[PDB]
Image: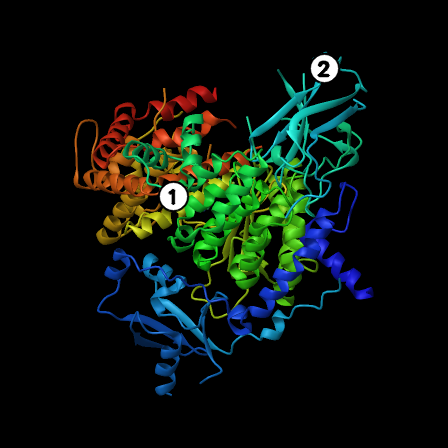
Amino acid sequence: SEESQAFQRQLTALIGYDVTDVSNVHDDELEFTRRGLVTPRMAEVASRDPKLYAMHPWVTSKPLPEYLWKKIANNCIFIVIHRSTTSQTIKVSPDDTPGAILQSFFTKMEQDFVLRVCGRDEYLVGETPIKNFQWVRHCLKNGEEIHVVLDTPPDPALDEVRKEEWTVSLWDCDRKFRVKIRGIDIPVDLTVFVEANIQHGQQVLCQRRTSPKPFTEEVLWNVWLEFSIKIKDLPKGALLNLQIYCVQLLYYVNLLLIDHRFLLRRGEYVLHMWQISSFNADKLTSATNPDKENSMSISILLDNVRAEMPNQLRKQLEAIIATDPLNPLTAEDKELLWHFRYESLKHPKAYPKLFSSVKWGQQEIVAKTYQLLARREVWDQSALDVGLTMQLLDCNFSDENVRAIAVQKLESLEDDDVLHYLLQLVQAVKFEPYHDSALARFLLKRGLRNKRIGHFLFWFLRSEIAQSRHYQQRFAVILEAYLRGCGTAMLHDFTQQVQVIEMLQKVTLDIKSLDVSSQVISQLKQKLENLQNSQLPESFRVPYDPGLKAGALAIEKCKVMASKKKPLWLEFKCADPTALSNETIGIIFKHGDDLRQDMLILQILRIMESIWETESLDLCLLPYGCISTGDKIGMIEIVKDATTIAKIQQSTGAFKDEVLNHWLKEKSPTEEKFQAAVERFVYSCAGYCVATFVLGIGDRHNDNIMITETGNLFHIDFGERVPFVLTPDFLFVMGTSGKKTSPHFQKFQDICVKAYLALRHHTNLLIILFSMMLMTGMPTSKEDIEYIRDALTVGKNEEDAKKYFLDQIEVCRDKGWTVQFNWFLHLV
Ligand SMILES: C[C@@H](C1CC1)N1Cc2cc(-c3ccn4nc(N)c(-c5cnn(C)c5)c4n3)cc(C(F)(F)F)c2C1=O
């Protein structure tokens, strides 16, 4: 009771929003969701293994790729066991477990000892072979020794959870639905009218506009908008979308007609409306505008066996199922899908198109859809198609049972795969009608089960709460629900992290107020010293990479980055002892820009890598951690031994072909290291040429493109033209110019086609991730989404796609420096 208020105030600090507050509400759905999420939390906390939770072994049941088998010498992975300034190497095979390795060590000079990684809080533990650990695969990929420290396991009592102290709609009639629009109000384009839509999954079932009156401070209509749809006909999660036009949309607000308790909405509502800045995720929100003083408001009143198909039609049905998600279904396609629904149900890929064809505004039709969803032996037995699963969780589907079967397929995901899709799955909670949902419980459950997922779950939820008024109320209830079962050790760790972000965001606002200058470098090193002496914690877990513990600031190494945005080049000491080297943990702390759009671009690029792993292609674009920490701010990994090619080129806008290759000659001393860097350049450049072409972000200036000393190319910014950057300086490194060819350029083409075709095998997955980004990330249009189809070349064989992408390579070679030079013209 007394201490619970302090614990509640502790949660509010971590969450960044007061869940107990009821200023911006008209119902108890948020409070019901807090109470509702008690059951899945305590079940998941009870079911989880205490030992494996504390140690959190990051593993994958996927196969090891062909390129990583060639890194293994003679079926023998070298693993070095360290123990208080004494190291010993062991001959261990890929199929051996940690338990087998422990027995092998303890033979040559027992139960209460575990193999922790050197430097990181990462544990080689549990009934899993040594190749399946993701740290072991990272060491073999990058070409580094697997250094391991022998020590006692962490205590599960540190992860203790506290004691927590806590179908048909009623008034069913055959009458038509109506709403009285009383009027509107605002304190601070000379005509307006209210448009009352009845939406269900971005689909207007009925629409009734008011009469056009003049745009004054208080416009009062006082009129029943009588619709032609019954009360029984209203489906669950039906959305009363109220909008104010003037041709020109000004304001909007939504209201759920059927509530969380299966009851129809009634009584007086003065809903405070969101202002506009086409369709997006913010358009769908049940939350009202919290800023009640300035915002627009709207006052309302609510008061109340089977035969075989023909061969033509089966071919016609299979033709409809074969098309992509963005291919629009006609009225003829929907009627065919519905009439032959039991044949459509035998194909899993039909499901998005089938449940799009449902007439959700008829109660009898929804009942048949539920009867159809009952017997789904094919869907349950099918292999996990994540792209197909992601379709059913987008804006087009509002039914709980349709969305629940998608979430059911997500249950079979391993923890490694959940991390790849976690950001997008957290963004997919915006498309839910209700606060409590199957997806919300899935994210909670898998967050509570694994520490790594739960770490990134915290930051994805906390970032949205900060920079989105539309969905902060939903995410705070989910985040509170995670934090109430994550454990005391993690609660302590998240507090230490938030304190570092809070202090650094306080420091960074003052620096931007005060181009490079003498005072700016001194004032930063002043402020970083002041916090470090007392207030700043002794250590903290790195948000983008929770294995690393960053300690105290190396304030001599700290600086402000010389740009317009002025990000903070911070540099921390490694807190955990027994590290390999004495290299500092470098962190760029970004501020000012909205990172939400760019965070989702990055996560797709990480999904593109995992596609290229499954078909044996080692491109490895994007070699740095990056994460959004709050409102307009973020935290990014520094790559040691790396610079921008604009710095390399000029060492006014005069470019050079030879200079980039001479830079690689300088930094890599030997010819084997040089040819490795030329090879790594060919693989990475081919990855970026393919990836940016698909996403439509290839035309770019060279100041935001970087290259490591090891040859690995990477990008630090995302958006008479070129489809991607393949300039003469890049082509020179391969060994060609103008109208010539070479072994590396031929290899670049072979890698480009293989990588491009590899992405085409997951066309539907990439389409929906691209579609979900533009709605959830950006505060868009159908035509913006339709580019990726043309970029992927949908409905064309591998020879035509090869010919298509090879032509786009030749476009870059003809123009060359024209696009890069045009930045200097357009600069002036
Ligand atoms: C897309 C967005 C994302 C939403 C945040 N991103 C990603 C990103 C990466 C890096 C980066 C990452 C590793 N390294 N390693 C380095 N050595 C550098 C280095 C040395 N000098 N410069 C000039 C760079 C670096 N920069 C820097 C930036 C910056 F522009 F904010 F500063 C952003 C940035 O805004």
Residue 473 appears in view: yes
Q: Which residue is mark 2?
A: 211
Image quarter hosting the N terminus: bottom right
Residue 554 appears in view: no
Q: Position of residue 388 (x, y in %)?
A: 42, 44
Closer-to-camera residue (141/340)? 340
Q: Residue at x 70, y 36 (%)?
A: 173
Residue 306 is marked as 1
38 lies above or below 51: above
Circle 1 Cα neighbour tier, 10 Å, few/some/many (<14 / 14–19 / ≥20): few
Q: Say what secondary structure mark 1 lies in.
A: loop
Closer-to-camera residue (564/289)? 289
Left or right of residue 716: residue 219: right
Q: Position of residue 184 (x, y in %)?
A: 78, 24
- Total marks placed: 2
Q: CA distance from mark 2 to mark 1?
A: 51 Å
Closer-to-camera residue (95/540)? 95
Q: Position of residue 415 (x, y in %)?
A: 46, 59
Q: Residue at x 39, y 25 (%)?
A: 653
Q: Earlier in the sequence, mark 2 or mark 1?
A: 2
Residue 344 is marked as none
Q: Say what secondary structure mark 2 lies in.
A: loop
Q: Mark 1 is on which residue type?
A: Arg
Q: Position of residue 213 (x, y in %)?
A: 75, 13
